Amino acid sequence: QQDEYTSAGYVTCWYQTGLIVPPGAPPSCTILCFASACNDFSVRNLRDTPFIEQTQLLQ
Amino acid sequence: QQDEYTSAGYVTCWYQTGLIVPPGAPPSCTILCFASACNDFSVRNLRDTPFIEQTQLLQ
Image (cartoon, rainbow over all chains, first blue to last red; front, top):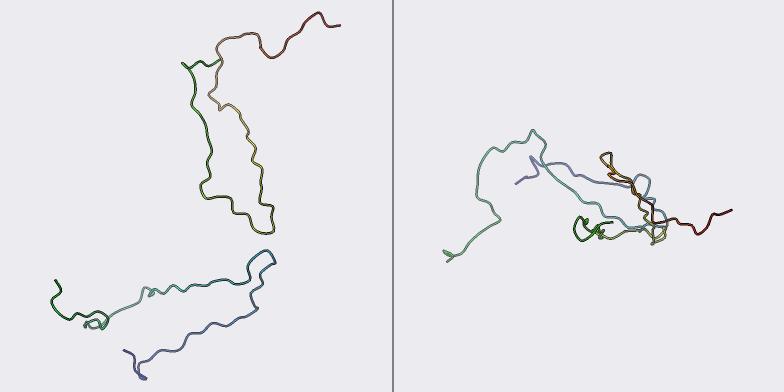
């Protein structure tokens, strides 16, 4: 839960030359992003995930 | 001269994905078949060829 302190820098992508697509191909293209930690990654504490919840004993 | 006995199996070719040809190229294409025996081929007897014939002494 990063605060202004212990935060991380912005990441951005900008055109350098401009995509050059020939007449026979569609001009638009789609780029996708894959994110995985490098080998040197570590965790330090353990806590409840604030993503899943429940209300009653589900039956 | 294969009979039902000592006959050989059928050979067939089917589309797996479908030819994908881009706008700049012609959609139709032509495939050709080359047939040659592998190294292990053998013949056993000798006989007249039933493909060529004659009528008289050609002069």
